[PDB]
Image (cartoon, rainbow, N blue to C red; front, side):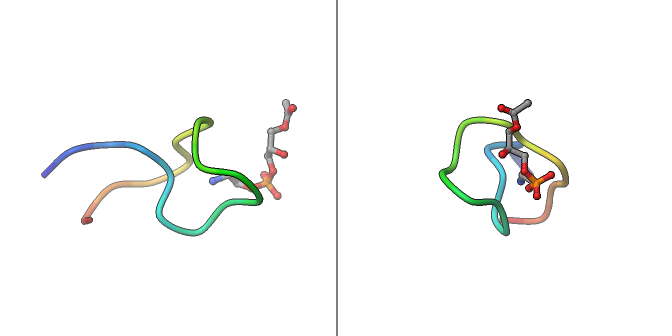
Length: 19
Ligand SMILES: CC(=O)OC[C@H](O)COP(=O)(O)OCC[NH3+]
């Protein structure tokens, strides 16, 4: 999977993976 923050405020922090 890739890491690009799937549940963040914007989408550039990356606090998790699976999307
Ligand atoms: C360090 C900074 O600017 O914070 C980045 C985001 O706002 C972090 O917010 P958050 O931790 O509530 O969401 C997680 C980001 N996917």
